[PDB]
Amino acid sequence: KVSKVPTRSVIPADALRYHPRYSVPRKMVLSNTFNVVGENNRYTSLKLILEKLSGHVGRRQYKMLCNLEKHYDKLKDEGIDWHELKWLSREELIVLFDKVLHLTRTERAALLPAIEAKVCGVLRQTDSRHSTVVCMNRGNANHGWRCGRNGHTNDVYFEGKAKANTAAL
Amino acid sequence: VSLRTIAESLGAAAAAELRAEVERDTRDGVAAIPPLPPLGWRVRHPSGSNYFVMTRTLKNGVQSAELNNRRYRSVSRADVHLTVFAPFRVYDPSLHDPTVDICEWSSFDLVVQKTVPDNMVANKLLQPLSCTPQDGALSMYVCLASVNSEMRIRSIQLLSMKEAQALVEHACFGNGEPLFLELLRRRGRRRPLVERRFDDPRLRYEEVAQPQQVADEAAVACSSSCYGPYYPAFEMLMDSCGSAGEYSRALCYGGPYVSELSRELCDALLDYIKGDLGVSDQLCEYVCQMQFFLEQEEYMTWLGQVQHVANAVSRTA
Amino acid sequence: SLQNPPEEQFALPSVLLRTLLCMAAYHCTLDADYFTTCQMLFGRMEQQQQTTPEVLSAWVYCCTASGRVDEALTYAKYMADCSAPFDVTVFSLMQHPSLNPIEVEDGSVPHSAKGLLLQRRLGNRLHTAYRSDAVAAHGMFVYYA
Amino acid sequence: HLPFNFDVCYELGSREFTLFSSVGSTSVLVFCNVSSRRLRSVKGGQDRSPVVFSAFVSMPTSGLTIEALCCSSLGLLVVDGVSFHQGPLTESMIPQDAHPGPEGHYQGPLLNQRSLAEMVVNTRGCITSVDPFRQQESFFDGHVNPWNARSLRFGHVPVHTAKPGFSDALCHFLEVFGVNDELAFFVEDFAHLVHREEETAWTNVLKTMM
Amino acid sequence: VSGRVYRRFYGDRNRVSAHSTMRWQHIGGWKLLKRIRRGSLFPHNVPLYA
Amino acid sequence: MTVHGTSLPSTYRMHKDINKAQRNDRKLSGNRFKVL
Amino acid sequence: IAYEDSFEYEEYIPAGGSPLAHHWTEMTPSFSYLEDEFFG
Amino acid sequence: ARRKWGQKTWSPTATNGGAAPANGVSAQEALQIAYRPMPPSQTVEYEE
Amino acid sequence: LPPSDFPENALLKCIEKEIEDEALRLDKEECPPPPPTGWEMYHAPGTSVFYGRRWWLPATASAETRATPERHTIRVQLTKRDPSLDPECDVRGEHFPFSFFVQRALGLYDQSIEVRADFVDGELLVDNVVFHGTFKTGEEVRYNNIFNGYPGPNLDEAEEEVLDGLQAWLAERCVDDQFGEFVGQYSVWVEQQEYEMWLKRLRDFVAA
Amino acid sequence: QADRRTRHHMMVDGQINPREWFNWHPKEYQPWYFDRHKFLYEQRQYAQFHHLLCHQVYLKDMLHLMRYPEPYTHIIDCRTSTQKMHRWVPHSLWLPRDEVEYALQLSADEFLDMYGFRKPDKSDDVILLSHNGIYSEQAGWEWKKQFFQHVYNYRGGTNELFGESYSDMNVSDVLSPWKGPFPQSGVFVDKWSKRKVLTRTGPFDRQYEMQDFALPDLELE
Amino acid sequence: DKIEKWKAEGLLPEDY
Ligand SMILES: [Zn+2]
């Protein structure tokens, strides 16, 4: 007898991702600072998305010319979050981009792929304690632009932690 | 009032960008020398264009090539005409799909034609030669690609006047193709663009209009040939610049899958193009260099056109 | 073992490419059939290194020492059309059909340095009122003499 | 909502609408080709091709015609390329009724890094397969075949991606001719109106056929 | 199967709950499975780890 | 700080930054069909 | 002919699938159009 | 002939030590391995 | 072929070697595969598109007095693939795209119903239904564009009322998975006959 | 300008294939201190020529020899281009940097016939000047190649004395972004190491280190 | 010298 290897006809492309043991990687829970969503924890998803939009992109490491990290500090003292940025309409973004942020035409052109997709600002789990991975799935308006998958439901700021509790903040 | 200060801000920025562009490639007063083509190749680049063509004529067959002439010292047939079309199309496919380990993919086309001279005596009429423009006008369209500085063949097409006659008369049951006949119905000529001559230095001052002479050598031979009214259908079939020529060459066979061929065939076809025909990896590395240099040359003309437009607005407003 | 960015890592100095071709051009004096390998060498130095007036002026001296009279002057006329000055170091070495340039920079010949300085200064003189093809054609006349 | 002086030209059956304007001796022409596959929502959140159009602003005082490749996102406007053509607005330059404009000309540098910014948010581009002959089954279609799309630079990514301080003045230079975000908010909403009117006409034609 | 039962609460989405450790050790069967030997019942409604 | 010149909190931060490209860049979406 | 009596089963080449491009039988350079001039 | 991806043609064996006889090879068998069918336009042959 | 005047003895001897082994093999058929009934297959010897054509008469009720004959046309383009992306890009999956024209009673893109389908993994997958010419709705809707004409939405996202009426309209026209296998079988014979002519035409070009 | 993309084929590894072929391995290189702020010939790549560096004469010593010169302290100007010199440093003699390698091979008489002044003896003090001190430093190595015991260098000679803002204009040859380098075009090495040498981990504007060998650390886990 | 060439090439036209 020669047994056949169990394969599939239709397999998703993320199943070809590499692990050094060819197994499931470890899912380490986040730090204790992310337990209660506060003013220090609100803008850490806004911090990381503006970091990836300014760093090198791709296998050839194409440097993004516009630095969107200079507009991070003027975003958080206003009190507007990345989740609050997705709730802004088209009329409210033109007021934010021209008056408050003073975003140029090329810096607005690089931030708009992050706003047109409604990327959920949920800190995904990683193998490390310090996670720099955000869920890049497109959000839906029924679940508060949180993409509704893997437990990212309508107030979830961080995976594995509690809700937003917007009565406090 | 506000249209003057906007058009003057762009004209000052375009003058500063062009000043900073020529300052980068300047080496102690000397401007950027273009890359040198191989021996015998005469590159013609139209100004304000997306492409550049180079020609090569091997007299007395392929035995006059660079590899067949070098030997060790101190111890007839029909002529071959080469034409390499090279557009500016070069992209990186590892961004759209990270599973592909390709840093650079640049496509360029090669048209090789043959012409019988009156000087050969040996093989006059033993067999009727089908490569002649009098008899069929057979030509090989070898679409090439430069995959990380390595020449890879995409398709090997064999097109004659018969395939242009078949597509225009009896590609369907009783008619031609309804789209190939429609594309021939909309053929407007391009305005004459001033070409620039980045030829080989040894053939830069020998003769200038030699690719223009060899372009009309086959043009008067094929329109006055055995196939007379099918040459406008054949020129658009051999049109390497545009979407109508790529669709018309897609209506023909397009050659077999080259990786499905025998490995003895793939090595012999690579020995023919690189070794015998002279279209080698020295040229294949040069095409991506010349696609890069003339992209820089067209960017400065683009910066000159931003300054020329913005200065013309503010002087009228 | 130390890797710079590849635009700075694989860029040899222009004095090395000048000395490498001038060793090859001195070998072309003793045997003219060395030009076919120098043609393959210059075919790779042009595509890997930078096309400088130093490496082009040495290639004119490479074509001169092989006996190629047509394409050596035609490469020099290409430098004149590109506003590239002819190198005065290879111009003094073209009019000296001895003195293999590795032992010239070493200092193995203490004499004839006044002769080396004179050809460099007239090459500085001839470039002020003429182009690069006129300087190179003067060097080819003295070399074949 | 509509801009100040712009006429709309749309016939049922074709997925194209064209906007024209003329101020003084200069004329600015905006042509759009609505996608048949799928267009993105105006809300943005939840194959989803963006609404990308062209802007031809002709100025006889300069002697050139500016082609502006514009992409409407969330009602706003970005510009991917600027090229220049000879003479005024001839009829052959506009890609109406599936005949293209001038081909074999320099497309222009990248004014913005928008397409590389969509790679970090994992939004799929128009190039779905790296094989160019795989997408050449539906030839003469800009949305399905990017290798012969004029608006997508025929699949080519240029060498120069222009300076941010330089490209900001180029965006302000075109916004005085009516290529602002007020125009792109109408084009984003009219493309959803063409996409529904083309689909309900194609359905009711298919009802009477069977 | 071979499962593990923990004493403290660890939810499927978050750790926040309304129970103490003294409550959940009776809810999730940590007090149950500690005191019973083989041949007895164990609930399926309680979470099993690994 | 004497022998190695760095600290263990500073070691973990620079370790996460020397390989940022090969850690995670895409989502690897799509479906792969069997060709055989 | 069966698989067990084949040349691929005499070595360890599999029956069907992708060809072993780094095997020594595939790395043997073949010239079948010239063997009539050499071994004839 | 032309090959297809995933489809291979099975061929009979010569039953002479496999493709390479590990026990040994004689003179006249290795004579054919010596004068291998190389293209002689780019092949230099030499003996001493 | 003496090597002095003919330096391409590596290619010319190799290609005439491959002409005969593609002829002496017994897996090939010199006869074309038999079509389904009614279909006549035309193919230009130079091109890579072969056409099918048949006449057909639908089933009409007795309230209608005359049944008009139809015109069914098949257009198959041969699949192109890029070997320059190999072995890095994956092997492209084999499929057979074709076009199905329906004309009521003279060209191909005037008053014609065009249906684009793919035969892949032994089944038909209908992609789009394209119209050409002026048709009746419910007014008249004209589709005069032949290249960038509106092909309709993809039928995965279409309505289910238009889906089940189309499959009944296709099964009545006898275009199903058994017809799509002949399109896959005739495309193998067409590409094999074009490959043998491509080897013969290449031998005239290189030896000249 | 405008951020020209490069033609080199360096690429970071993918997310699917395993890490293999560890007889070559790229890693990031970060040195201890910055050296971009320093003088050109005291940087990291010129560290082997540290003892070849000439002794520094400063500004107040140059003003002292201006007022009270010595008969055998030869101030020598090493500026090359005659178009960029506008004023004369006092008690100076013109010896251009491109001719130093031929000047010091001359005799005592031939140096006078080719430069108009007497050749200095090997025991006297020689002080070299330039625009920034780069041409005088390269001439100082040629003056120390010959057996001259006292060779000195004023870094920033012309730009500090005359207050000018000039440069020696060293090109510091970097490949143009169309010039594709060596390891992409060539079969000089096998295909596995060719792919692994061209691999880099991160952006290609910083410096890297190539390991010639590696062993797996089995003692972690 | 480049802007002088582009007016001769016709890339920088005059008033229409
Ligand atoms: Zn999510």
Image: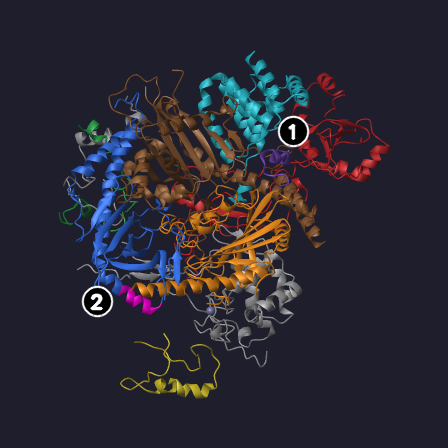
Chain colours: B brown, C cyan, D orange, E yellow, G green, I blue, J red, K purple
Label 1 resides on the chain identified as: J
User: Would you call the spot at circle 2 few (<14 residues within 10 Å), some (14-19), or many (20 or more)?
Assistant: few
- Nearer to me, F4 or G14: G14
Instruction: Locate residue B137, reporting x and y percent.
Output: 33, 30
Q: Classify residue D108 as left or right of residue I204.
A: right
Quarter of image, res J139: top right
**Residue picked out by circle 2:** I61
Give the answer, above or below, for where B88 lies relative to C51: below
Instruction: Locate residue B230, reporting x and y percent.
Output: 34, 34
Give the answer, above or below, for where D77 lies relative to A32: above
**Residue picked out by circle 1:** J145
- Nearer to me, E41 or B239: B239
Amino acid beneath label 1: Lys
Q: Which residues are magenta?
A: I159-167
Instruction: Locate residue G38, reporting x and y percent.
Output: 21, 27
- Nearer to me, B312 or I133: I133
Q: Residue furthest top?
A: C145
